[PDB]
Amino acid sequence: NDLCFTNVYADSFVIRGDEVRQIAPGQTGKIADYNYKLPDDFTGCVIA
Amino acid sequence: SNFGAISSVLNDILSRLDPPEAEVQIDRLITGRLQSLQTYVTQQLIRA
């Protein structure tokens, strides 16, 4: 809560519990595999 | 010389590692090579 970001996205899903980290830069796995992906930048959070 | 990375071949770094980190090894090689070029050109100037 210091700068103003201009645009944010409401992105969400659910996981296999096991990989509560698949959502991470380049960090691999079935979600980063044929389910989803994260940019190497991803100025964001995996708040979950 | 691998300047402290795993190896000194670019085709070898990509084939055993994931691009999240790969950049670090690559950057290492980059820095080393770059310094080498600097040294060569500087001594060339002095000799010239």
Image: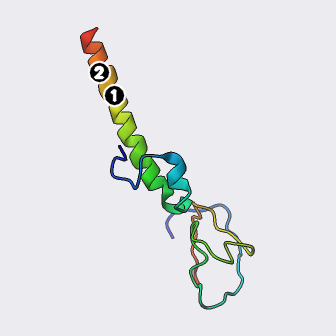
List x then y, in percent, for residue B45.
30, 14
Going 47% across and 46% down the picture, which residue do you hit? Answer: B9
Chain of the residue on which disc 1 is drawn: B
- How far apart, in angstroms, are the residues tagged by discs 1 and 2? 6 Å
User: In the rendered view of the protein, which quadrant contains the C terminus of chain B?
Assistant: top left
User: Which residue is label 1 attached to?
Assistant: B38
Which element carries disc 1, helix, strand or loop?
helix
User: Which residue is label 2 attached to?
Assistant: B42
Chain of the residue on which disc 2 is drawn: B
Which element carries disc 2, helix, strand or loop?
helix
Say which amino acid is labelled 1.
Answer: Gln
The residue closer to the viewer here, A39 or B32, is B32
Going 58% across and 62% down the picture, which residue do you hit? Answer: A4
Say which amino acid is labelled 2.
Answer: Thr
The residue closer to the viewer here, B27 or B10, is B10
The residue carrying pointer 2 sits among few (fewer than 14), some (14 to 19) or many (20 or more) residues within 10 Å by Cα, namely few
Do discs 1 and 2 belong to a common subunit?
A: yes
User: In the rendered view of the protein, which quadrant contains the N terminus of chain B?
Assistant: top left
